[PDB]
Image (cartoon, rainbow, N blue to C red; front, side):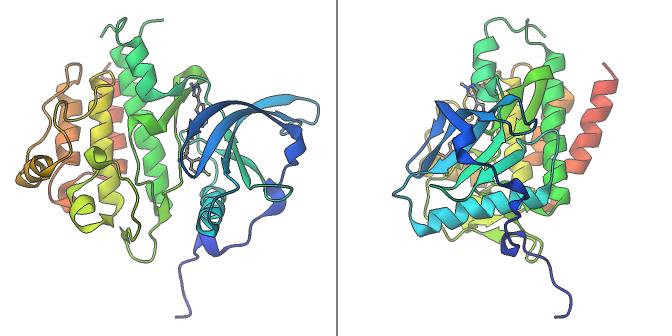
Length: 296
Ligand SMILES: Cn1cc(-c2cc3c(N4CCN(c5ncc([C@@](C)(N)c6ccc(F)cc6)cn5)CC4)ncnn3c2)cn1
């Protein structure tokens, strides 16, 4: 074993990220859960010494178990190893002393795509949301995940609620709390006992707790359905129950959403192949959508 995969979570925290927490002023809460929250904040002198900048800050509550603190640090280390990409919510800094650990990321001023699509739903036509916008969002998300996959990382919670929108109609993948580097094993088996995004999950993830590059692609197919339905909930009217799992196992798939081009529903159908090996890669999806964009 003289050659090994470098586990990014085993690498030392790089203090190049460190930022004084008293230069942050917290604002509105952007998301919250049992373990912690993400808040809007002003960062004084973060990039330029004399300028204030709006950021998002991720934090655990003081009651958070030791397991949660290490997990937030592991997320920080994954983001540090991944590096910058246009289509992810990038790491900007961290506060690792003087209080609870804070992870400072880019702030996306339009919020999550799911809520955005639901707002623009009434005024959509194929500042009006158009089909060109939807194709762009599909392309940008595929580019972001191709980047993640090229770094041997899986996200494991891809969904329109975890895609954010910023200036210039740029979409960024967010929430890397469950992202894993799967270099060594080519998959990840989840040993946890958390609430899971069942309607976005590949059947092998539901039934065998197996997560792979191919299960991220399944979720991307679901995301496309959210996108071209302008934010409808997946499997409308179907609760998550015995019948849901049975139908998924037997091959039931959502039909084409109202505004999806035939070539985009073709992508979703392949993303939802019961055989993971028959699903496209994100690199293939990027190329496919690139062709569709250039044909207007
Ligand atoms: C109305 N509006 C909204 C935005 C907006 C929203 C974000 C954003 N997000 C916020 C949501 N997210 C998020 N919420 C909760 C968790 C937790 C609960 N699971 C969690 C928290 C801390 C922790 F230690 C462990 C888990 C995780 N993540 C992140 C993405 N990031 C950037 N800009 N931005 C801009 C803009 N207008």
